[PDB]
Image 1 (spheres, rainbow over the protein chains, first blue to last red):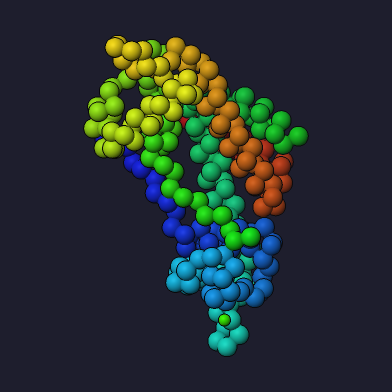
Image 2: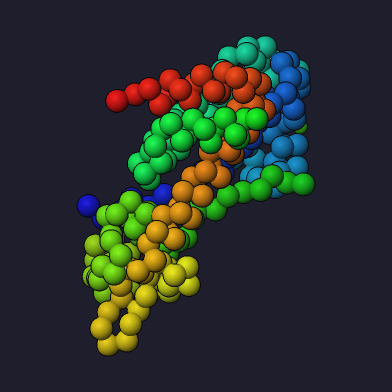
Length: 119
Length: 121
Ligand SMILES: [Ca+2]
């Protein structure tokens, strides 16, 4: 019954998040060359092992791919990355609204508020 | 220009957060007596010192009051706390909608989505 403590998000997952969001927001486009593990480690001040762990994760999620001799590239399957991103965001939307109606805010007023926020 | 790295939220502030939400949601009510630092440390399995930092901060935010020789108590001003908690969630709400619009989702769609999410029993 003791409270759950949230830990640091691992640094390698923070970098996955960053690259993924950059793809979703078109800072990084489909088939763009991504820097090397070295260049990323050097630019972000992150241990190369952590960057390599990031890049492995990103590849598993199909956000990036490697071409032998040519380096690491943003996937061509970039619409799929954007949709998964929106889903992360929609999950968050769902959760804030739930916590709002739980805080005593009625739905009809959440509708009004949202309409104001969007106007 | 290195990316910002987000650290662990200090445990004392996670406990500050936990208690304000209980207040916000009427789990703890106005003027309810709070356990001692030692009893909270045993409930939440935290260092007593950490719980002491949490209590000290909850008090700075006027969420709880330590009245000498008697105890530590939830504020009488809980409607204030409920209102700021809502504001926090409302800030989170425009943040997520902002970010959905920037991930290319049209606002008219977000509007429909919110209705769908809200249509649930
Ligand atoms: Ca290199």
